[PDB]
Amino acid sequence: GKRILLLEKERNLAHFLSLELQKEQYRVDLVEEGQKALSMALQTDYDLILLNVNLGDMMAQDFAEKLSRTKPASVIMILDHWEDLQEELEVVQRFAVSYIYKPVLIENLVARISAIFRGRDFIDQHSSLMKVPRTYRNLRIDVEHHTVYRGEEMIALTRREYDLLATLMGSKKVLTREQLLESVWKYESATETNIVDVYIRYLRSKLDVKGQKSYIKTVRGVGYTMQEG
Figure 1: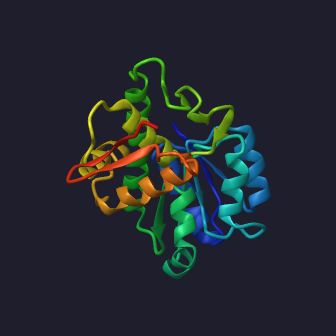
Figure 2 (figure 1 turned 120 degrees about the vertical axis):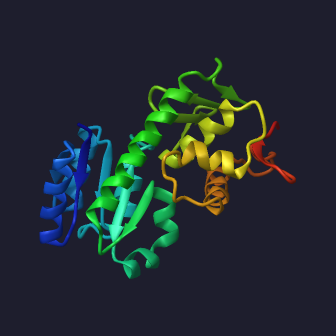
Figure 3 (figure 1 turned 180 degrees about the horizontal axis):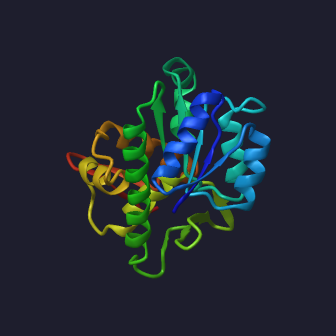
């Protein structure tokens, strides 16, 4: 089964989530602080890393940035109280594939994790069919390693940003926000179209060079497409 790295500060909840996730045949490694979580995530490829906003010895944002130096498309999901998540909402959107509020309902957590895994699988399969060369202007995508480069620099795209780029680069046509939702949030049927604009903004911030045309064009009345220089 897929492998989950789990850090939950509430002891009884951590134990509960560990046991319930193993009933889905997932392999669950429970850790209690970020330093240990980080050493484990650096040496093992986890399919999901499930964290609180604050890991105790560091913020989850800090963990994610440090992990991203070698594994930029890591799949991190944040579980926390509403007030804790909202205090850090913008930074959480930037590094996490999803977030979920306490008090958690296990059937909901299980369904969401399943959908996230299936959506990543879809992206992988679809991107394997991308026309070669997988380049655009100064960008190149390494589909095997889920990495992106602009010139000779690695661009630390998050998993959502990577999935969004692969979807845009793999399309010959302008894509609507509904079509982008259907590809990048596939199987996460509760996702709504305004999230697409958020991640287009994030993706532009990572790709774009000041004084060049953006890598992504907004097409009036339609949606988004890659943009030439």
